[PDB]
Amino acid sequence: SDVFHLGLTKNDLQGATLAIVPGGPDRVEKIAALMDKPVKLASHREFTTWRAELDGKPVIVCSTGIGGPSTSIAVEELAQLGIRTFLRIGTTGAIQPHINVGDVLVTTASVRLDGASLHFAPLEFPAVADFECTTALVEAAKSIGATTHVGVTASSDTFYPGQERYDTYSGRVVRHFKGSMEEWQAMGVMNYEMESATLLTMCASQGLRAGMVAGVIVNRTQQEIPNAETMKQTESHAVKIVVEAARRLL
Amino acid sequence: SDVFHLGLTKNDLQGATLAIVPGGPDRVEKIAALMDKPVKLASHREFTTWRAELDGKPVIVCSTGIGGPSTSIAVEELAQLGIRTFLRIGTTGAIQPHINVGDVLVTTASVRLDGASLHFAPLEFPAVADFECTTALVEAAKSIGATTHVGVTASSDTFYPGQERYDTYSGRVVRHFKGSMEEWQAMGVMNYEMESATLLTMCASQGLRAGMVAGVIVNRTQQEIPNAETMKQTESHAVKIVVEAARRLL
Amino acid sequence: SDVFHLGLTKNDLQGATLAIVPGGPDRVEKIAALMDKPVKLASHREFTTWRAELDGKPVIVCSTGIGGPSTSIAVEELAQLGIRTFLRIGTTGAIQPHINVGDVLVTTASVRLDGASLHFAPLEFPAVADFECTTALVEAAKSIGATTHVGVTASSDTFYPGQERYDTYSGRVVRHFKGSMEEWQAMGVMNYEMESATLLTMCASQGLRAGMVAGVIVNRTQQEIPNAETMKQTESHAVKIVVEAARRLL
Amino acid sequence: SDVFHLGLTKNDLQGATLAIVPGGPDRVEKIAALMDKPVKLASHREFTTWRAELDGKPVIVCSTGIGGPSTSIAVEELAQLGIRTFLRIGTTGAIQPHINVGDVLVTTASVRLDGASLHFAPLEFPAVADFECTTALVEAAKSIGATTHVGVTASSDTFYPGQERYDTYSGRVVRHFKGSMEEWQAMGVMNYEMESATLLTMCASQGLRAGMVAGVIVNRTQQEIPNAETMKQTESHAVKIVVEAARRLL
Amino acid sequence: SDVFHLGLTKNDLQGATLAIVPGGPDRVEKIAALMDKPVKLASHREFTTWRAELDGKPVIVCSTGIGGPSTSIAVEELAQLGIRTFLRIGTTGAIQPHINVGDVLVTTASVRLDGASLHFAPLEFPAVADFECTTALVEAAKSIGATTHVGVTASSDTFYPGQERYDTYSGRVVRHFKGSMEEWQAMGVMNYEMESATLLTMCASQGLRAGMVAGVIVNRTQQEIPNAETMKQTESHAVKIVVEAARRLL
Amino acid sequence: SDVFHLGLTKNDLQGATLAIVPGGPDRVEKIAALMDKPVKLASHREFTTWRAELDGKPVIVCSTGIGGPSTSIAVEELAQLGIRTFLRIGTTGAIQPHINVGDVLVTTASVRLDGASLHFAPLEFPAVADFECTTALVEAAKSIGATTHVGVTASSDTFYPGQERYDTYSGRVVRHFKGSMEEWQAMGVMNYEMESATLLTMCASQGLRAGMVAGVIVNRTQQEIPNAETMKQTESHAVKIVVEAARRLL
Ligand SMILES: [K+]
Ligand SMILES: [K+]
Ligand SMILES: [K+]
């Protein structure tokens, strides 16, 4: 293989220059399923790669795994194989009371609560999305009548203390993150996830285009018994949006 | 006056909720002249305010002064007066060799090389522009046929060592900023200016919309004798763009 | 003109090597008025420059605008024109209960809550005043019987959250600055202003002499209806002191 | 399931309180095969868990994924399931010229070049291994006659720029990490990997025991063509060591 | 003398390569007294050096003074004279309720709340002890039946605010250290002392072996009238342990 | 004793409120010999205290030890005993080529290269000397005809890598401090020593007066064989200056 981890040789890619990069292989398969001729290319550790075709152009779909470090390997190796545009879709807990479960969020830029972004640019650099990608995602969302919010996302290297969860083995949060959630809420941050600050920073600092969209599965500000059926629909909607945005970027 | 520095009452604004915020009064008057029924409201220190009408709605134009600190007083006091949308227009030196004098930059987010942004959000929070405002500026640029780049800007608390200039009384640059220019170049940063990291961060973190456009009057990467008429024309082009974008945000 | 912003050509200066640098042009005119042959030299953006003569030697007076960034341009360009000594006068809110309105404060060194100082020296370097300048200011204050306090000042890039004001559009202060005021009070800081950390650091790090004096117009620790007449007298007193100190430095 | 990601109930663990946590499932299965009555419990995303018996006690083996973020979810959720001892086994590139391929490293503590460790303890807290676990790994290494080094490891959120690799799409490394490798070399750091600063810090700071051993598959300081069989044998040796050490901690 | 401060010429040392480095000369004399042929070599400022012999090999004992700076001079100059292994013994206040007065603590690594460690390695590097030294100290403690705890220690440049003591001239603690003690307790830190972060970091970063042991004289978590007699016994026990560990390292 | 380390009761001080704080006891005795009725009060560890009379008022002279940590214990415990004014005298290596051996430095404020100052005030707070004390030291210097420089000093937690010395066991300096000396040189820093950033910050932030003077015994910028008699004479000159300044502060 032409790269170290993903097990992909460049002609495998058939000249593709856009990849969709969700977190896990299950969703890779769902996204491939909305395009033509889906074929599984490789599966090695957390990286599962499919190829498909969209309006006659090849598109790659490749799982990142959880967190910026594995995200950074996937984006780096796809770039080594010629990918220049990256779009992430995920699911997310919102932290604003006006955002509802089933809404869609388009991330303009992220609060860098990760470690990998710093390996690309010092903290003062913005983890900002590419304007074309963001545009395609906002337009795509409107093409299926999604309720959309466009704004900042907080991107944490942890699922638990970095998102100020206390339902843990220790039940406490280190001082730097204690009270962080309410600061991010006051500053209008939409939601937490775990990979965007790494994704956006490494692309924006290296001449790659990236954008990021997510469906809301939980609203942290209001207790509510999760509805598995709403979640599955929300996921399906966010997948269509990412594909439709790719269509507009090809 | 209803505010501490601006010498403005809310009554003066006649219900305006959008401000164009250039740096200097000469530019204030130039922007207002493009619009209908422009009148000077006040001038105290570096803050000069005019009111004008655009498609029949009142709009404020108010100078920030140089740098994040006076910017931060203008923005806060206009917000206190009911402004919720802020558009900055500037003129700038580009640091990328593909960007020419006369091109227009629209800033998606800024490298925080200032101090005042930290008084609003820790450094990990992105200095990012509002999506609607960036969309309107990009559309306005296209509508006059401008050659446009959309991207990251470095926003410095100094004109000289923070922009890595050596043509100074000291002729040197402190260690932290020595070599910085080449780093930002490698990371695709378009240009330097001195107020956007303050404006964008304090707006993004307080639920105010902001965008920023600039005309290129210099290219730091190419020696060339400045053309005083080219610069005037580029200023004209940027001013028209910012008025057109405001038209789309009213 | 010999410099980029101030619009000054060096022979304009007539060999001067000392400048007084207050914030705004109104006060430039007041300070020029206490010396011989005052003549206005230039006015461009927030920088208004006069020249006058004191015991037969030329002195420049030049407004800085609000905040370290514009302060840094003025000091830099005056230095390029041969100024080697800089004295600032301003007005200030004190934060200690033993300091009264109408007292005068002489700043030995400043807490660096600004951004521009870092473009001259890393944060560990002290924003300290020059000993001769400080001496001339303390002696000058005593020559008109002023009640004087000599000590540390906190120098903020913002007027509002950085000075822990809550009477704002957001009515909140970011976590790093929330509770900061009471820390500075406990540590004996006299007052807040907005330019000294930039002024003192850039001069002390570049072989220039600077000093800083201010009249107290407000005491933050005790509510009190401002008396416009006390303020005007205090200002006039602080202007005489700065001039008289310059006399001792020439 | 009793946890959010792992798909495990406490019942599944049959009272296990020690986990071996390698990076990938292939290694999970290889570790479990060394022990008695191994059975697969669950596989979701990058987390694959088997149970097995060692000297008649249940032991869990569960993959972390690449990087501190997914590591941090595995460790937290196993802790929630009653795991109190964690042993990591990895394979690694050494950066010291006295360390050969096939040698074993046991890590006393790690250089924190990751983000997730900060979500547990500020950077001044040591990423240090539990003494009993390090003792058991050193004893286990000696018991198979391994050539062992005991020392500090650098733990990076990236495989590429944080390990100072230039064979990349950008071919460059941000200023902070340029030259870093030589610094760590001078300071005696044995090797790079990507999860130990997270694992050790979050265990050391929450009263969980952790240790870490790795087999050397590369020496970055010596060009040499990789031998695919040497690497397999080194992986075998490291796996045996980690099982033997677990034997001593049960 | 061969060095700048300690007043020692290398042949004085008779080929020794291990030094015990307690804080003060009184204890130097106590430690020398447990070995053969103790002879005082020098006394200059806080550095008092004796030589003695242990199983026929020369050992040096040299006081460090209080705090990392003087500790850093002593270790540096002994290293210039050929010492390669350093063992510190001291006395300490514990901050955990399960540790009793008269227990012994062996430090695996330290929280860096000092300044000197940074002059050897950036903060992310662990202030970790050498594994052999730590082993010899744990084994030595067990050889006299000591109640031992092995773990992390917090190493402060101050005795008072850095250890969160309020019984002071100011009776307050600066914000960064206010509430620090309870964070360190939650994270399982055993005790405070003042030299280990400097000692461990400078040795671990420069190929020197160091270890650190201490007897508990106070337990901060429970008020208790100090018993001078328990303290003296505890000291005598900790001295025997350090000597006995040296025996195992020679 | 009324304090924990110094072995002093308040009674011992006979109402003294000024201390001269040199580094070592030999200098303690030398200072006291200049004054009337000097008597040794106590000696424990690096702290040796004498009392003496100056113009009929009791004055304390007490050694700090090397470095901010032991300095910080001396200053705190003398403050507890009623000392409110502290004057340090040292001997130092200059780093500017205009400063000669035998010159006297008076420090207006210090570059904080230590750890203990942070335990009193964050790094943005200036390590600045009290104006009265600096005035008295400058006056005392002039009164004996000393060649004096008044300015910034760099205060390091180490004698070796923090002063950028390479004549060491490692012969190297960590990245952060490599090149630092030249930076401080460019920024006009006069000299290095090891206690002033601690002393000045902790005094300035707690309402205690402090000043600092030093005699130059080396010029790092000029190779020259040290003259043992020149150094003794320079020490004499500095001691006389500090006693004269104390005379003016009583
Ligand atoms: K992962
Ligand atoms: K300004
Ligand atoms: K000491």
Image (spheres, coloured by chain):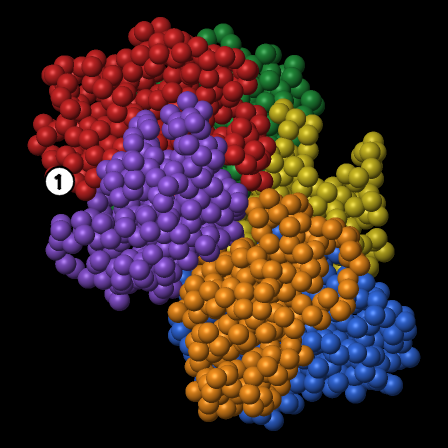
Chain colours: A orange, B purple, C red, D blue, E yellow, F green
In x, y percent, where is residue A104? 60, 62
Q: Nearer the viewer, residue B116 or F42?
A: B116
Q: In the figure, is residue A178 to the left or right of A111?
A: right
Q: In the figure, is residue F59 to the left or right of F152?
A: right
Mark 1 beta carbon near ligand 2 (under 8 Å): no
Which amino acid lies under the numbered mark 1 shown in the image of this protein?
Asp
From the image, tell me which residue sits under label 1: C2
In x, y percent, where is residue C148? 41, 13
Q: Residue at x 80, y 39 (%)?
A: E221
In x, y percent, where is residue E2? 45, 52
Q: Nearer the viewer, residue C163 or D125?
A: C163
Query: In what quadrant of the picture does the C terminus of chain D appear?
Result: bottom right
On screen, residue D53 above or below B244 = below
> Can see residue A123?
yes
Q: Residues within 10 Å of mark 1 (few under 14, many from 20)?
A: some
Query: In what quadrant of the picture does the N terminus of chain D appear?
Result: bottom right
> Can see residue A119?
no
Q: In the figure, is residue F229 to the left or right of F125?
A: left
Q: Chain of mark 1?
A: C
Task: Give the SS element for disc 1.
Answer: loop
Q: Residue at x 59, y 23 (%)?
A: F78
Q: Residue at x 54, y 51 (%)?
A: E117
